[PDB]
Amino acid sequence: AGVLIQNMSFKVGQTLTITGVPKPDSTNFAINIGHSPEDIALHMNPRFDAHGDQCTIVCNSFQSGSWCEEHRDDNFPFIQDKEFQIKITFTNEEFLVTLPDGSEIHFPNRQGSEKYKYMYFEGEVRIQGVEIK
Amino acid sequence: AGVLIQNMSFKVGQTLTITGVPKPDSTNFAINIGHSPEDIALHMNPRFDAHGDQCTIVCNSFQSGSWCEEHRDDNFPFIQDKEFQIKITFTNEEFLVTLPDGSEIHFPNRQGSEKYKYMYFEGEVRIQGVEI
Ligand SMILES: CC(=O)N[C@@H]1[C@@H](O)[C@H](O[C@@H]2O[C@H](CO)[C@H](O)[C@H](O)[C@H]2O)[C@@H](CO)O[C@@H]1O
Ligand SMILES: CC(=O)N[C@@H]1[C@@H](O)[C@H](O[C@@H]2O[C@H](CO)[C@H](O)[C@H](O)[C@H]2O)[C@@H](CO)O[C@@H]1O
Ligand SMILES: [Mg+2]
Ligand SMILES: [Mg+2]
Image (tube, rainbow over all chains, first blue to last red; front, side, top):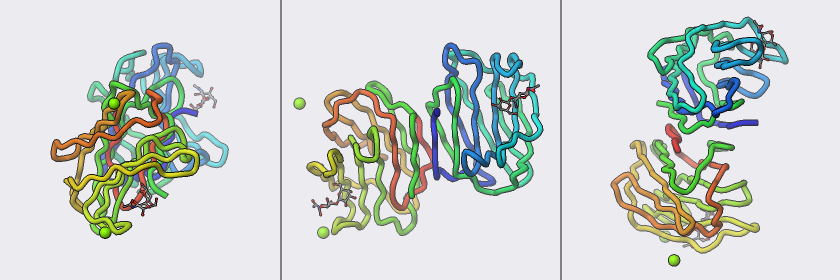
């Protein structure tokens, strides 16, 4: 059940910096930001090869047993066993993900909250750094 | 009640860097590194004013339902509402804690595990940074 971080508050206006390395045999991995395992505002799922996607980032939200509408990005600067740094900023309106290569993903903050105290990193990735300021 | 981090891996050779800010009226805060809540290899507990202690760092370990012997340090480079960075290195022998001013604390690795997968931050502090 991967890396679980509880009560490290991520609020509107801060940057979340995630340092990690996909496992050498990674098919995919996910960053889950939300309130609980049943209420995820941002599911960000870089897929090397999983769910029928190859080198695709799938973003979605999960609430009350249900996945919502997928956002898909073909921009994929992740490599098996290579360190990455991802930045996440958010507003009431959306998450702004800055990827390693300086490119960006815009995903709506559908849950609408200004503070999230649940972070869950799942799948074939090692998390070396979580920074919030 | 405070920050719980499970399955982030701390190992001999690695630097653990904690970044945070004690609350303006912080009495104390604690960095817990172990296996479980019942098995704590390093409890590092800077006390502004708690348990009769002012401006003291208390280090200890918790196993089999008991605190072990305290290591107490009068060196206190912490200020309420000011950002700190704390670097922890460990070996089979000891945790080497590097304090914000470049001073160090030696605390024995009484557990002797070589890898820790449970971290719990307690008390009046904002944890801003956890990197291994
Ligand atoms: C084009 C396509 O549909 N693929 C989807 C899958 O992406 C989807 O897989 C789940 O997607 C959610 C996020 O939307 C999580 O990543 C979850 O772990 C995946 O299983 C599947 C199942 O919902 O449906 C489609 O086939
Ligand atoms: C001088 C002295 O020995 N005082 C101790 C207290 O420090 C101690 O309080 C506990 O200390 C542990 C670490 O050793 C934890 O920080 C815990 O939160 C404290 O309650 C008490 C109880 O063990 O014993 C003496 O008073
Ligand atoms: Mg006293
Ligand atoms: Mg010796």
